[PDB]
Image: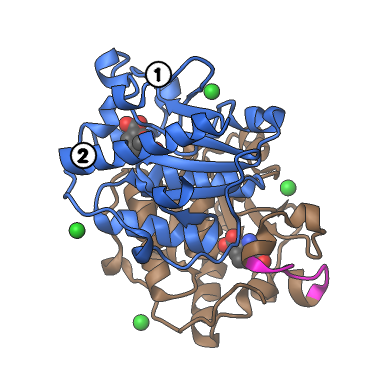
Chain colours: A brown, B blue
Amino acid sequence: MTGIPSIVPYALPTSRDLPANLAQWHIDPERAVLLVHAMQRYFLRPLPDALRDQVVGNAARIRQWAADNGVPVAYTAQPGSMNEEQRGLLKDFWGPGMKASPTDREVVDALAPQPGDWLLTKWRYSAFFNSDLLQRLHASGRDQLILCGVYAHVGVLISSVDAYSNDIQPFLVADAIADFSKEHHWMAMEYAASRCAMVITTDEVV
Amino acid sequence: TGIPSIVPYALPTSRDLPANLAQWHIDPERAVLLVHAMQRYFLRPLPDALRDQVVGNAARIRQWAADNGVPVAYTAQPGSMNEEQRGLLKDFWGPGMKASPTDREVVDALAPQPGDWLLTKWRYSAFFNSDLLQRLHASGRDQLILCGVYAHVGVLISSVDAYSNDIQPFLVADAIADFSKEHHWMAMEYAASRCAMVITTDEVV
Ligand SMILES: C=C(O[C@H]1C=CC=C(C(=O)O)[C@@H]1N)C(=O)O
Ligand SMILES: C=C(O[C@H]1C=CC=C(C(=O)O)[C@@H]1N)C(=O)O
Ligand SMILES: [Cl-]
Ligand SMILES: [Cl-]
Ligand SMILES: [Cl-]
Ligand SMILES: [Cl-]
């Protein structure tokens, strides 16, 4: 129903497993925002537990780093219970989607937003789409986006593409993202590294 | 170019396409044909035979478009992008093509005709800082048939963006080309499972 397949568990990439970055960017905490992409209960539910816990543990470490380094933390979250118009073509792939219910829509407790964090609404794959993300990045004078969350090859990648397209340098945190499969997750990193983003590991940010 | 050396490969046929999850169908009253980045600069790295096949199929879909009153939209970069325009494209793709006709023209076999939508390509999405969405909207068209290059880059990202805009995209799998068969197949697989119908030229015509 969810359109989200059964997720076959897999090991997260380590530093050694990343594709070669073509861009030469580096996170500057004065320039960066940490995008915690779609770490809603609904989206993490299909992750097997160990992998989920690994990914979320990494995202959490990056979040604390961002807090320590004055980097805005932006959470994207679908509102739930999208009507048929709001859902649009998401229905065809992903069914009606999550409910506007805490069981579905809350960001997971391990990543609980803190006061002042950017709470962004997710509508489509790109975190920019119909969101305030770009405007906030401009206002905050932040032109780097550090991405963690789910799903690597879907909103995370497409958000990184959009960021890139908007001349926002994206950094995909390879071990703070998770995906439908190892193959997808690797595909996402390969795409990002070769097309729109730096691919890095959590340890490389902190 | 940052465009890798392209390893020739055979274009997919209907049998080779991934399963479509969506159940859409091209309706000529609803559709626009996007000829995506079929500029000489972007076709130059293609080996000739593959290029000719892709261009030929694009040309077949173009003709079908014209015969069915489907607007044909060409995207094309302006060439010689300045720093502001080029942005982070520089880091992946160098300074890009020149504004010379030799680079920037739409290939002759796909020459735009009077009336066709001449859109400017800036970024991977054909919608990015273009007029595509506004034109789809004004023209009442909510399907986008994509051909062109590169499958996994602007074609796919254009499809994603179309999709995200509730514009049903149809990826014409044999009227696109890419940096490699693996990219091309990845694009089709992505599209079919996330944002588009993947179809062949024959299935349009
Ligand atoms: C976690 C993401 O959200 C998409 C993917 C699966 C299901 C979805 C839904 O039911 O709305 C979302 N369109 C992401 O974009 O990566
Ligand atoms: C054919 C496309 O254009 C991008 C990819 C390769 C090189 C480019 C450049 O030099 O600007 C474009 N950014 C496409 O988006 O697929
Ligand atoms: Cl594994
Ligand atoms: Cl928002
Ligand atoms: Cl082949
Ligand atoms: Cl335009």
SS at mark 2 in the image: loop
> Residue drawn 28% across and 18% down?
B98
Between the C-alphas of marks 2 and 1, the distance is 20 Å
Query: Residue B129's x, y, as percent?
Result: 55, 28
In the figure, residue A112 lies in which quadrant? bottom right
The amino acid on which the numbered mark 2 sits, given as a three-letter code, is Leu
Q: Seen in the image, is B141 located left or right of residue B60?
A: right
In the figure, residue B188 lies in which quadrant? bottom left
- In this view, the residue in front, A36 or B10, is B10
> Residue drawn 55% across and 56% down?
B195
Q: Seen in the image, is B101 located left or right of residue B25?
A: left
Instruction: Identify whether B39 is placed above or below A21.
Output: above
Residue matched to label 2: B46
Secondary structure mainly formed by the magenta segment: loop
SS at mark 1 in the image: loop
Q: Seen in the image, is A145 located left or right of residue B12?
A: right
| Mark number, residue B78 | 1
Where does the C terminus of chain A fall, quadrant-wise?
Answer: bottom left
Q: Is residue A97 magenta?
A: yes
Where does the N terminus of chain A fall, quadrant-wise?
Answer: bottom right
